[PDB]
Amino acid sequence: GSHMCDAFVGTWKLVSSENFDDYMKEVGVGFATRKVAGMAKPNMIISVNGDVITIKSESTFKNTEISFILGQEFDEVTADDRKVKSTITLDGGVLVHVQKWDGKSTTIKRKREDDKLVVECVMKGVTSTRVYERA
Ligand SMILES: [K+]
Picture: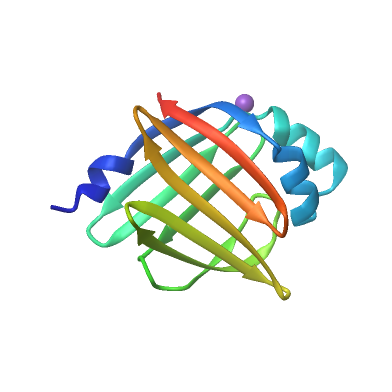
C-alpha cells in the first residue's frame, strides 16, 4: 500500500547529531544562530493528509512547517530564514528534499532505519547527519 505514511508519520525527537555546525556554517548561518540552534534538539512531527505531507519542527528556539506534495515544487522558508524553492520526492522509500536558492542547492534525505529516522543534509562538500527516535 502506501507504506510510506506508516514509515514516516509520528513524532520524532532528536537523539544524535554530527557535523551540524559545519553544515549550517556552509548553508550560511550566522555564528550566534548556529550555536543556539545547535543546542535546541527539536522535535520533527510528520503527518499525512491525503496527498499532502506535512513536516513540523518545534523547539523552544524556533518552529517551522512545510506542507507539500511529492514531485511538486513549493516555496519554503527555512529555520534560518532563507527564502528557498523546495522539491521533495520519494526514492527507494527515502524522502529526498532539495532546496535551491540564489544559485545554491542543498539536499536533505530522510530515511527510516530500524526504529530510527536518519536525516542527512548535504551542502557542497559538507555533510551532516542527525538521528531521531519516536517520542
Ligand atoms: K529545546
